[PDB]
Amino acid sequence: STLEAEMAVERKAVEDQRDGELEARAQKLEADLAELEAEGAKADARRKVRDGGEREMRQIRDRAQRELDRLEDIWSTFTKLAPKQLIVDENLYRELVD
Image (cartoon, rainbow, N blue to C red; front, side, top):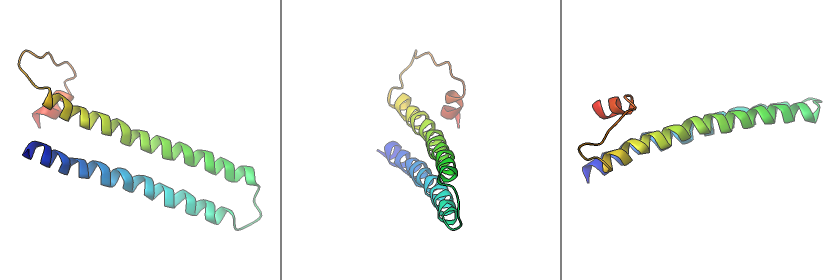
């Protein structure tokens, strides 16, 4: 119970900054699009800032995602921990060491 409790406390460090980065770049590049609509600018250039912004949202969000599935994967292998279980990864193993 304390394992899943402070595991969930670890998931607070997952979810809070996991959302904080996407809100950070979201306010950053959407505010950048807000200043982009000030002058006379071609709309397709703002669509290029939009597409690069989608690369930032999906890219940073997928960096968050591999941390979600890797980090929860640590907890899964802990809940699936038993002897004679052959483990290869050696970094996940360090994630069991620390």
